[PDB]
Length: 609
Ligand SMILES: Cc1cc2nc3c(=O)[nH]c(=O)nc-3n(C[C@H](O)[C@H](O)[C@H](O)COP(=O)(O)OP(=O)(O)OC[C@H]3O[C@@H](n4cnc5c(N)ncnc54)[C@H](O)[C@@H]3O)c2cc1C
Ligand SMILES: Cc1cc2nc3c(=O)[nH]c(=O)nc-3n(C[C@H](O)[C@H](O)[C@H](O)COP(=O)(O)O)c2cc1C
Image 1 (cartoon, rainbow, N blue to C red):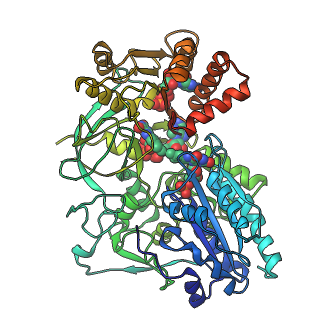
Image 2 (image 1 turned 60 degrees about the vertical axis):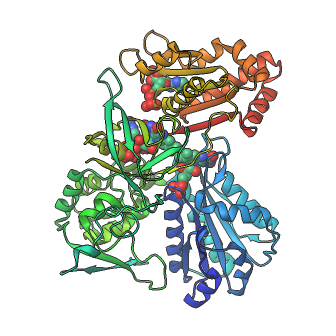
Image 3 (image 1 turned 90 degrees about the vertical axis):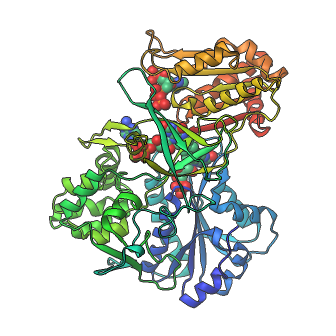
């Protein structure tokens, strides 16, 4: 429970702001959009600020009308089971319980979500609906960003209509480059005051002190890092992180987050192509001395450290980044292409989508392919988004491994249409960790994916490929429960891989669990061992009769882990078909039945894409 700042409205009054944009963000996307809208205000003669709702009391919204022509915008992402982001949970709870009168308040909401998930943009939709129920008036339509298509474009389209709507309503009206930070180079800086990759307090990585979390990650020693797949088509790995003496608690189903380091070669080349000295110690200080965000990342620090541990230099740059960088491209045609990247349609948009996004060109690739583009290193560092932690489904049970967190991951490495080979940041970094000291900054995030409280409750686990991760923890635990003399209900695993001799993960361990009876059934779909595809859902359909018995009569809990794009939906459709045949009942009622299981905690998801 953080200590709330004083009234954001009073802050706005003292700083001359009329627009405030709150971000409900988990991996920084909403935060970036909010910063962009906040900065846009200036171009229309207004003034804005972005803010984390967790740091404030949104009840002060009722005082916003005290500021003339005021407006509040919410850029909100949705997470686990249509829930708010962790930083927006307090606001969400307040919205549900409050009865405050928001008459006079003007608002707009841009939701960030993904159509492949169950509750698409649930948080954005809720906030938009609730503020109106409380008496506030909507100044622009709810934006529904879909990350399954192209979120950046949905944001661009919405933003392009939003500002004119705001200008028309408030009777205001609308061209230069403005920086948020000023560069301060430090000649004789004490090393003790220089950040070298820590996320929170200076030297927190060196002097570890609990409790450990996102702000203060625990550096866990990699005690094991072995190749899991038999073949060489890809690289799947098993890692074991030593969390001894960290006081960290976890359960099977939770997630472990890690803070990686970017590839040194990429960092070196960015500095090289820009002709910058990456070992310069500096700070980027907010030109707005009132803001709580004094720096874009921990400072003072060297550009090398920033590019390595604090900045995202691998994902396709967003349109505002390319737009601001255009000024540094001396070739007219290149300046024109970069400027047009922010277009909401036409050739400029088509180029952004194909040449930047589809081609997966990162910032270095763009600097190389538009050779006249040579921005100063300090401004680039202010423009780049923050390097995010990566989440992995803990693949161990704390009942069996209380002092170790296991990770099952596939290394990301692919040929992009940009012509170069792109490497996943976290997986390339983890793959290179050699036991005995290889340390990994991490923390555990509690999830709602959990084994049944009653050991006798049957469990149906569906997790092809790396989706098997949490289930290794589940199986370890259920096995442990049997070894403890407890009565354990049926435990069925529906796993899938390409070929038994290519990438059958944990083949030996699973064989052992099956032989010992920890696994009532080990159903494996080898998708490429025959001409037709054989997937986990084909096996579920095969066992429809028994599964229905377990679900309708045995109160079984279903778990689906892995690909959220196609697998999760195909599996869900199969469960619909099963319920529809044995209920019996029409598709519509089958869908409703399965939806209910989810609300009753008997159908859990741990999917990603
Ligand atoms: C809740 C949750 C649980 C997860 N559990 C696990 C897990 O247990 N095991 C696991 O392996 N992963 C899991 N992940 C995924 C993991 O967090 C990372 O996204 C993954 O390891 C890649 O990270 P990276 O830094 O190596 O790659 P990044 O540098 O982040 O690159 C990822 C991006 O590469 C691009 N890309 C990948 N392949 C291609 C391609 N062939 N063509 C074009 N683009 C491509 C995509 O845009 C992808 O988003 C989980 C994610 C979430 C959210
Ligand atoms: C574990 C996980 C769960 C998600 N659950 C949902 C969901 O229920 N509904 C939805 O619309 N989008 C969901 N998304 C997609 C995000 O809302 C979308 O990617 C958003 O752009 C993330 O914004 P952020 O970076 O500001 O947190 C999920 C993403 C992850 C990684």
